[PDB]
Image (cartoon, rainbow over all chains, first blue to last red; front, side, top):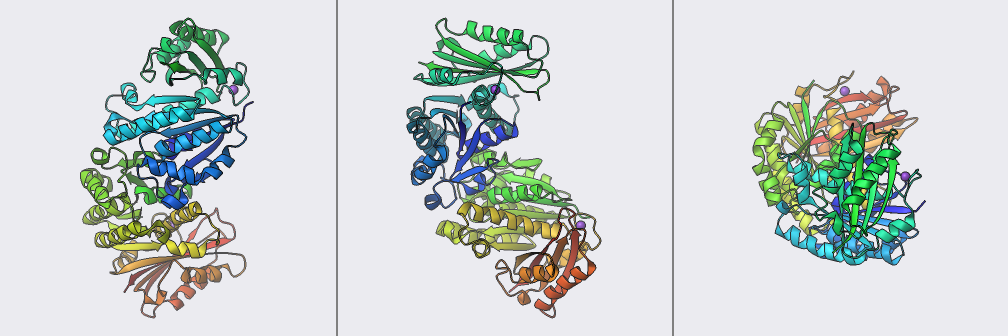
Length: 306
Length: 306
Ligand SMILES: [K+]
Ligand SMILES: [K+]
């Protein structure tokens, strides 16, 4: 199985890494990277890497991408050494602030230069976060795209379409953390641990080598008709904010409990295939999570959008 | 038993509250309060109070005490409602940043105006954090002193005298979090839960009503001579950065396992009394922590320093 590191960069990455650990996501090594020593000390990762100790003295980057970038530059030797040996590196961060925006591209570029298949999974800030955050996030996304093989972008505004109408702001942020965790786990669960219908690493690498950007969609369903319902919810997810038939590559993960059947996996796959372009390169796998009972989760990652 | 709330304000308070929860500190209600939604979502407290949602949009106060203050002002109705009914409120924060420095005094003043015995337990930043942090912390400490009954100040530089010489910066910060937890738990364990030698709430209130400032000291020891060794370490703690004989009031907590003896409690108390002024108002109690084996911890809180 592939050797996989998941790197949480800055506050958005910190929370996503903790959510993966809370969900007992197996087969990956976690590395929390941050300029903010207080936040870093709340990481559940065993490897906690403080960057920019001299520059920022543990105080964070103050929403300044240049300080995030220079912090990662300060610590480039340590970052390179931590990443050495990985076949694949996920770099997770929230865009718009200082450390995510500035450090995540530096870290991703280091991983990519080492030869790791490098996948960024990042949030674009909620519009309510304001103009400075939006502008800085656009800069980070552009930098991230240069530094990775595939960048999966989670449009946080779309979460607001998904959650209940009176959801407090704190809970909207909490859901963004969960979506980042779902983005990484959707891919890693199919390659990091044994399974009946895993994915071939080489095939993941091919779908993750497309240009342009990538998006994700998530569907969850229970009971009768769950496989079809979950798949339909995934392809119609507000998160997948382009028509899936525009994608060059599609990866589908269906996860269920021990009762997940061949018939259900096929049903879900057929829905996603049918919605996608006729000439799409689509790959899929299934995961048994024995902690699930009657729910199934379908995650779709679509790459190579114009 | 007294009804006690422990309020973690901003990043330093967040980490201290999590450390209390990790150490299974009983008998108190925890409330995490923050302008930073990502950090707040890592709180282990069941009550998570986002303040300044409109002003800061979940992004934190950017090391600006005025923004911390105005965030608390925005949310004053919610803060007042959360604090109603408490006999005692601990307000814990790191001084020097925006939310701790600015919001903690507002919150403490609300608690004090409600009639709660209000005790602040705050860190003064490490010198390495720089001049802006030092100056802002001095302002916060002055504000905090006006807003509480007793302010216990933890001089972070003194932690550097305590930890091993090559301790990384991240671990020095982690130890500050632990000291804040020890400051609160030293007092709360003697009044919040049943015990053989608890303290009288009225007596705690008297020692906590002194003017001037307060300091703490911690000593830990195992094996033969543990009670005397721990007590001596507490009174000579670099954290207690004034001669204990200068204090008007002294509170001592000795905590040990089920083997903690009357003789040991007395031995420790005698050491602290002997070191203190002849006319000191000193009170003490003991706690059995059945999770301890042969270690004992002595905590001393000294109040009313000139
Ligand atoms: K698997
Ligand atoms: K007790």
